Amino acid sequence: MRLLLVEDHVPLADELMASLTRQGYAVDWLADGRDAAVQGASEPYDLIILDLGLPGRPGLEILQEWRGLGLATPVLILTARGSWAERIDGLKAGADDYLTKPFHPEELALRIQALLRRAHGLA
Image 1 (tube, rainbow, N blue to C red):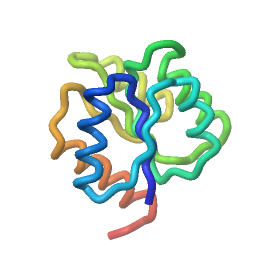
Image 2 (image 1 turned 120 degrees about the vertical axis):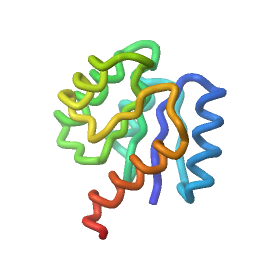
Image 3 (image 1 turned 90 degrees about the vertical axis):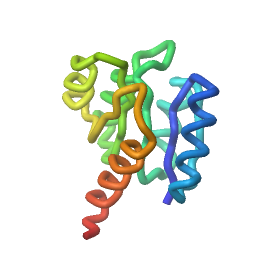
């Protein structure tokens, strides 16, 4: 099991890494969308966590590129406070689920669990 976390804000990345570690996951962290676009398509991950708040190339364009390459990896997007549009647009772009910032770690855990469960058809 291995996750990719794409998160530019270091304090948030550090918190997410700690939380994901407490949940039992090995995680690779990338802060830059250019790096993430390549690595997400090239390296085996069970799940990618993609913050839509990345500077530079929009996260949703990165996600669309991945889907156009046939990437079937589960993607959980982190969306903006109060943005219903980002959740809808993110699903349309090919996200499997989302979590609205600021979020609670229990909800992070539950949504990741469910994606990983369905990905393997686990009970």
